[PDB]
Amino acid sequence: ANAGQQVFIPTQSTIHIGGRRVLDLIIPRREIAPNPTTLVAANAMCMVRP
Amino acid sequence: QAGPDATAGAIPLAAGQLFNMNFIGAPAFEEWPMTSYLYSWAGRFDITTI
């Protein structure tokens, strides 16, 4: 008689693991270049920009 | 370079027009229509040169 949408919370979603709130990622440079000094150099420099 | 016989279109090619080469800075990628680029050189192909 009474259809409707219904919500469920997966058990996997509630397990607590790890503690690394903050991180830094080093990304490949597609060109052979010296370390960037400006913003645009750093943007052009990357293998793929995040 | 474009060939001797000029063509129309959204990207017209004047006869002998020179291509503007791509570079690592990218305000915009640059490119030509290909059927028109071949329409330009279509008259100059010749069996001795082949």
Image (cartoon, coloured by chain):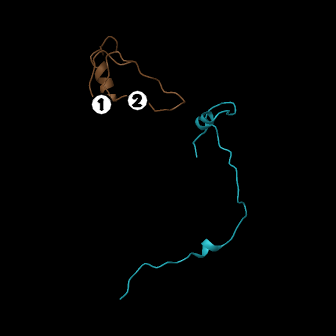
Chain colours: A cyan, B brown
Q: Which residue is mark 1?
A: B10
User: At 60% across and 71% down in the image, what residue appears?
Assistant: A13
Name the residue nearer the viewer: B10 or A31: B10
How dense is the environment of label 2, judged by Cα within 10 Å: few (below 14), some, or many (20 and up)?
few
User: In x, y percent, where is residue A27?
Assistant: 65, 43
Q: Nearer the viewer, mark 2 or mark 1?
A: 1
Residue A47, picture quadrant: top right
**Which residue lies most toward the bottom here?**
A1
Q: Earlier in the sequence, mark 2 or mark 1?
A: 1
* Viewer-nearest residue: A39 or B13: A39
Depth check: B22 or B37 in front? B22
Give the residue at x 34% y 12%: B49
- Up/down of B31 relative to B5, above or below: below
Specify the amino acid type for callout 1.
Answer: Ala
Image mark 2: chain: B
Q: Tag 2's secondary structure? A: loop
The three-letter code of the residue at mark 2 reads Glu
Q: Residue furthest right?
A: A19
**Image coords of residue A3 (percent x, y):** 38, 83
Residue at 52% of width from left, 78% of height from top?
A: A8
Q: Is residue B38 above or below residue B45?
A: below
Left or right, residue B11 beside residue A23: left
Chain letter of disc 1 in the image: B
Q: Residue furthest top?
A: B48
Q: Would you say B26 lies left or right of B17 here?
A: right
Relative to A50, residue B49 above or below: above
Q: Which residue is mark 2?
A: B31
Q: Position of residue A48 (x, y in %)?
A: 57, 42
Judge left or right: residue A23 versus residue B40: right
> Residue A2, located in which quarter of the rendered image?
bottom left
